[PDB]
Picture 1 (cartoon, chains in turn orange, cyan):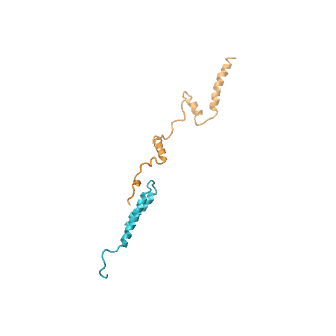
Picture 2 (cartoon, helix red, strand yellow):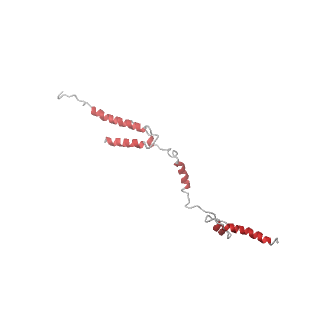
Picture 3 (cartoon, chains in turn blue, orange):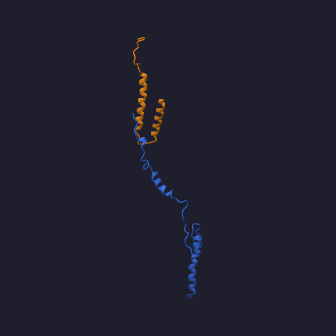
Length: 85
Length: 56
């Protein structure tokens, strides 16, 4: 007898599976995606964007800024020692 | 041929395998196959309409 009409009806496979949710996510995310992100920090300029760039970038974490930062406070109180003495 | 109809039918039963929510479409198709097979055996069973009057 005469075949039923379901095989030629589709209209809820688009909620029917899980990658639909991911699809509607990644059509927004990827379509308006940039090839590369914006920045790993770069502001501190006054001849100190260089200080941050050399020391406090993702390029390295090394003891050089620590030494520098320590020395600033040492220079304050060391001069003040002779202001107190 | 009849084999075109039936090949497309059984191929479609196995396509209907690859789609769910169509669990009785194939059962209708099976019925169509049955009666198609029935009409050929109906036709082979046949007693020709005319009486035999040459010999009989």
